[PDB]
Amino acid sequence: SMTEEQPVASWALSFERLLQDPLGLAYFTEFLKKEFSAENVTFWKACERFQQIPASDTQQLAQEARNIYQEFLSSQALSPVNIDRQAWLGEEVLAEPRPDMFRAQQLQIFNLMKFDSYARFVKSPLYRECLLAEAE
């Protein structure tokens, strides 16, 4: 009935839950940083950060847009996220920043890590340490 939920176990039930829960995302990002492939989750975080901004404050949108752009979306990006660049917006997203722009690209990353880094995390430490210790 969705009235109650599992403890940290809920992560292994749904990636959404893992990705919506601060603890889940934290431990997940604790692994995903030391080897530096956090670009996906932090891009999703960036787009989430972008949609967090009220469409009313287009100025903040403009600021965040150029941030995410130069970091992940630039041709000289320090963290090049793998999305369809060929048909990507480009200068247009700087021209008109709106909190619905990177939506498809956001879900592109979401589904990218959904069956990969997620699938790995539930097998990796930190999860178990917060889930159980006696095993059975």
Image (spheres, helix red, strand yellow):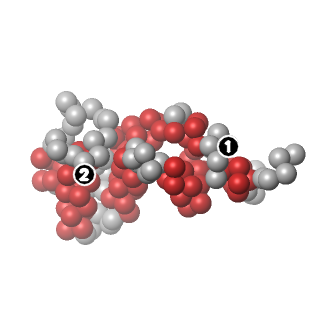
Q: Which tag is nearer the camera, tag 1 or tag 2?
A: 2
Residue, x 47% and y 38% (percent of image)?
A: 113
Give percent across and percent down for residue 83: 30, 35
Q: Nearer the viewer, residue 91 or 8?
A: 8
Judging from the image, what secondary structure is the residue with disc 1 in?
Answer: loop
Mark 1–mark 2 distance (CA, rounded to whole Å): 32 Å
Residue, x 64% and y 53% (percent of image)?
A: 126
Judging from the image, what secondary structure is the residue with disc 2 in?
Answer: helix
Give percent across and percent down for residue 1: 75, 50
Residue 71 badge: 2
Count residues near mark 2 (Cα–Cα under 10 Å), then give few for <14, some for 14-19, many for 20+: some
Give percent across and percent down for residue 127: 66, 50
Count residues near mark 1 (Cα–Cα under 10 Å), then give few for <14, some for 14-19, many for 20+: few
Say whether residue 97 is visible.
no
Say whether residue 68 is visible.
yes
Residue, x 58% and y 36% (percent of image)?
A: 119
Residue, x 43% and y 51% (percent of image)?
A: 33
Q: Nearer the viewer, residue 47 or 31?
A: 31
Q: In this view, does 28 lie to the left or right of 128?
A: left
Which residue in the protein does label 1 denote? 13
Q: Does the CB distance between marks 1 and 2 fall below 8 Å?
A: no
Position of the C terminus, as image quadrant, is top right
Question: In which quarter of the view is residue 85 placed?
Answer: top left
What is the three-letter code of the residue carrying label 2? Glu
- Residue lying at the far right of the rendered structure: 136
Q: In this view, does 96 lie to the left or right of 79?
A: left
Residue 86 badge: none
Q: Nearer the viewer, residue 40 or 60?
A: 40
What is the three-letter code of the residue carrying label 1? Leu
